[PDB]
Each structure stands twice: as structure tokens, then as C-alpha cells.
Amino acid sequence: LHKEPATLIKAIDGDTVKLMYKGQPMTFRLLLVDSPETKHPKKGVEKYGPEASAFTKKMVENAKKIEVEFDKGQRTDKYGRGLAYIYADGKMVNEALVRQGLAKVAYVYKPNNTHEQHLRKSEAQAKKEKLNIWS
């Protein structure tokens, strides 16, 4: 797997960010994580949704460098969003959310599952620490 440079355009949700990638504006969905949502009427503004959302936004907004890391599987989902691990100054946003109990680890579709074990490890610690979601 390799990291590629990208530029923040806009944070949209806890698990969704708009980036400039290879000169094109593109919406990325964060791989392997399920964040409470501020969007979708088939929920709405769920609990911790605004919290997960502010965490992703500060994290990408305050970074000097953002990088995208595609996994081994498909790189787009059916809605046209890129499927990636997103890094803010070397720190994986996907892992940070889960470590803070602000996301669960998603149902996982091989072969897009390289960092699966790492995140499950962070998710067990957040639950052990009874953080946010896990409170």
C-alpha cells in the first residue's frame, strides 16, 4: 500500500471528507469505520454524530499534510466515493476516531481489510476505556 498526497476541500461528516486528489475534487468515505451520522433521514443527527463530525473536521483542517491510502480491493463504492485510509500529518484519521470511541469498526469486505486488525485493537481499547459510544 502507498500514500498519495491530497488537499482538503471540505469535511462533510465524521466518516466522509471531500478532497482534491490528482487535480480532481472527490468525496472520500473512510474505510472500515462506521461513525454516528449527522446526515440521512433514515437516522438523522444520531448521538455522537456531531462529536464525530467535529473530530474529523478539526483533525483534517489543522493538518499540514493530508495523504490518502487506498486498500487492495475496489477503490470506489457504488456512490462514486473513494474508499481509503486517510492520514493527517502521519496520523490515520480512521484509527483516531475508533480509538476515541467515536466510531465502530465497519462490516469488513475483503480484500479491503488490510488495517482491520489494527483498528479492532483500537476499538477494544476504546470500549475497555468506556469512551463516548462505549460509555
Image: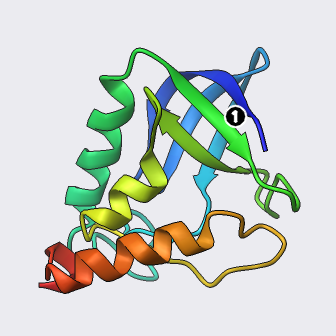
Residue 123 position, x and y percent, is: 37, 76
How many numbered callouts? 1
| Image-based side of 96 in relation to 76, left or right | left
Quadrant hosting residue 28? top right
| Image-based side of 90 in relation to 113, left or right | left
Label 1 neighbourhood size at 10 Å, few (<14), some (14-19), many (20+)?
Answer: some
Residue type marked 1 = Met
Query: Does residue 14 appear in this view?
Result: no
**Front residue of 97 and 10:** 97
User: What element does badge 1 sit on?
Assistant: strand
Quadrant hosting residue 78? bottom right
Residue in the image at 35% along x and 59% along y: 97
**Front residue of 44 and 97:** 97
Residue in the image at 79% along x and 51% along y: 80
Residue in the image at 86% along x and 57% along y: 72
**Front residue of 96 and 33:** 96
Query: Does residue 73 appear in this view?
Result: yes
Give the residue number, with chain letter if any, for mark 1: 26
Position of residue 10 relative to residue 51, above or below, is: above
Position of residue 64 relative to residue 21, above or below, is: above
How did the renderer colour the structure? rainbow
Residue 133 position, x and y percent, is: 22, 79
Residue 135 position, x and y percent, is: 11, 84
Position of residue 104 relative to residue 70, above or below, is: below
Residue 128 position, x and y percent, is: 20, 85
In which quadrant is the N terminus drawn? top right
Position of residue 124 relative to residue 12, above or below, is: below
**Front residue of 123 and 27:** 123
